[PDB]
Length: 26
Length: 48
Image 1: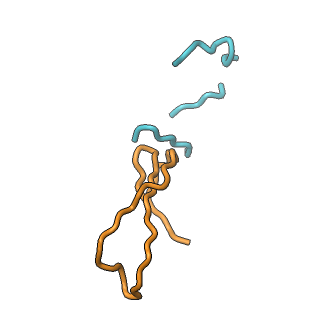
Image 2 (image 1 turned 90 degrees about the vertical axis):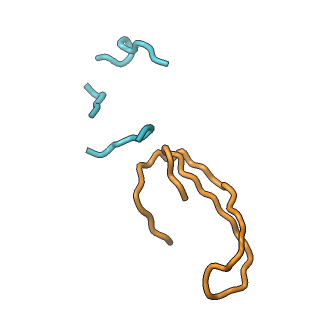
């Protein structure tokens, strides 16, 4: 499920670089 | 202990033995006691 959050989140604090894996290190 | 698609699975079985040497010859089974959606991308371990 996905919806447009421009009026809720847009204002530079949403970063991005096995299934269901989270890789937090940098 | 298994760790597949983030779901980490723990089976076990607690059973009376009378031997001091090593694993006794016979048969018994281990029933799942816990799954955890850990999602950790794992390699190794260590006992306490």
